[PDB]
């Protein structure tokens, strides 16, 4: 999977979680989101290829993925507790992470 | 001023930006939010009263204010460039910073 494929996985599985009503469905989708975020986590994106890996911009970009993974992990723990609706609300709050990184990079 | 005071300041002024009757109110409210955020960064939230100042919890709490301030500064630059509608639009996305830290520690 490349960056575009990883982002489509994140996009679609957010909606899977919204559509769901049980813990197994939400867990399955969050697990898919976690793998997609981890797949995209380490690559330097094209607009930052000329920046140093420790540059402020690259640091903030990598932190965007690390922080997204952290909150996916937290939502997954809620799903593993059978707390379906709390896990769904946590998943909805992931959208803040998506929009924050997009706004920086675009 | 204490943490509750600082949060009232942030809440009132975020709404001032949403409702600003004139463009100049936006920069004035961002200025007050910046100071409130830097003050709140020096407090201990009640739910973390039993945590070390070096705990990952207090680290993430303090970092959230640095990041909020960074995005307040972006909005201030827009308003100082006279791009006051862009600044108001940016201020809207500050709500994600509030929701994120609250999810953890409010
Ligand atoms: C940086 C730390 C990012 C995070 C977190 C998320 N995305 Fe992303 N996204 C990022 C890049 C560099 C790109 C490619 C360049 C571009 O601006 O398109 C993308 C692209 C997408 C896309 C495709 C285009 C679009 O419709 O916006 C989608 C659908 C997308 N991203 C979705 C998405 C979601 C749902 C995220 C959070 C759950 C998310 N992205 C996080 C960088 C980063
Ligand atoms: C952490 C980095 C935070 C950020 C960023 C914001 N807030 Fe917050 N807020 C935080 C905590 C730990 C608490 C609990 C404080 C307590 O003493 O219990 C709060 C609380 C509030 C409140 C309620 C205040 C009260 O009197 O109980 C409000 C209205 C509030 N916060 C508003 C607010 C807004 C609008 C923010 C974004 C602009 C924001 N806060 C950021 C921690 C953090
Ligand atoms: Co967090
Ligand atoms: Co940022």
Image (tube, coloured by chain):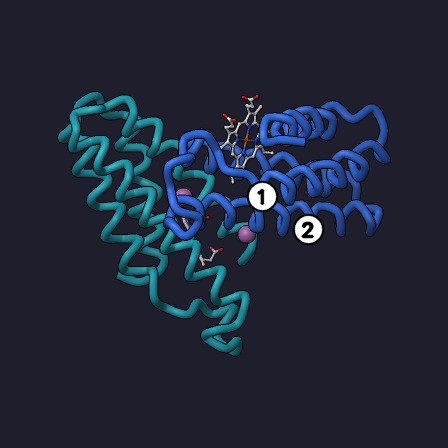
Chain colours: A cyan, B blue
* Residue on which the image places disc 2: B74
Assess disc 1: are there few (<14), some (14-19) or many (≥20) residues with their C-alpha within 10 Å of its C-alpha: few
Assess disc 2: are there few (<14), some (14-19) or many (≥20) residues with their C-alpha within 10 Å of its C-alpha: some
Find numbered disc 1 in the image and state the secondary structure of the residue it sits on.
Answer: loop
Q: Which chain is mark 1 on?
A: B
The image shows residue B54, relative to residue B47, as above or below, that is below
> Picture coordinates of residue A9 (x, y %)?
29, 47
User: Residue, x 64% and y 25% (percent of image)?
Assistant: B8
User: Residue, x 69% and y 42% (percent of image)?
Assistant: B34
Decide if ligand 2 comes within 8 Å of the CB at mark 1.
Answer: no
Looking at the picture, do discs 2 and 1 lie on one chain?
A: yes
> Picture coordinates of residue A20 (x, y %)?
23, 25
Mark sitting on residue B42: 1
> Picture coordinates of residue A25 (x, y %)?
17, 31
Q: Nearer the viewer, residue A48 or B24?
A: B24
Q: Is residue B58 left or right of residue B83?
A: left
User: Residue, x 80% and y 39% (percent of image)?
Assistant: B27
Q: Is residue B7 left or right of residue B59?
A: right
The image shows residue A53, relative to residue A92, as above or below, that is below
Cα distance in 3D space between marks 2 and 1: 22 Å
């Amino acid at each position: 999977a490349d960056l575009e494929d990883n982002m489509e996985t994140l996009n679609d599985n957010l909606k899977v979680i919204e559509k769901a009503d049980n813990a197994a469905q939400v867990k399955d989708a969050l697990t898919k989101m976690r793998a997609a975020a981890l797949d995209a986590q380490k690559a330097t994106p094209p607009k930052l290829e000329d920046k140093s890996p420790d540059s402020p911009e690259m640091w903030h970009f990598r932190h965007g993925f690390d922080h997204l993974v952290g909150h996916i992990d937290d939502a997954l723990k809620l799903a593993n507790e059978g707390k379906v609706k709390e896990a769904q609300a946590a998943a909805e709050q992931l959208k803040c992470h998506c929009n924050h990184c997009h706004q920086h990079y675009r």
